[PDB]
Length: 51
DNA sequence: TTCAACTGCTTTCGCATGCTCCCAACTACTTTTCCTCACACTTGTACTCCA
Image 1 (cartoon, rainbow, N blue to C red):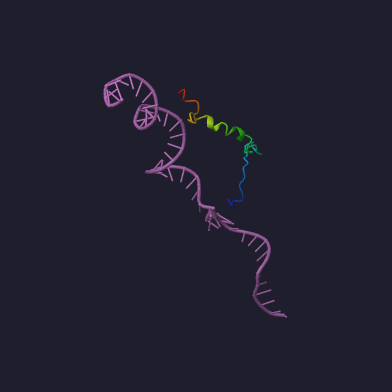
Image 2 (image 1 turned 135 degrees about the vertical axis):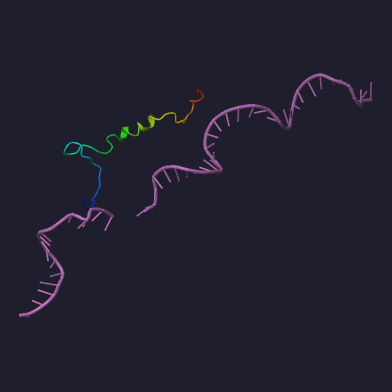
């Protein structure tokens, strides 16, 4: 389909004009929810004296 | 004059597409905190050879 010109990060989602892919409006709460799902990383200090 | 010219534009369909990793698999040495007791000196109480 012709020739590839460029590529930038916006996304049409509002049946016409676009409302998506605006950068780091959610990244502040992205990398503070990634490392709570898995558990028990064993970076343990006074803990395990107990366990 | 005589001649090319190369640029411009148009149908026909259309064929229609062109600094080097990032992560697996091997492996290895090192990382991290724990664990159970040897060495040696010293101190005691004794009985020896002390005049």
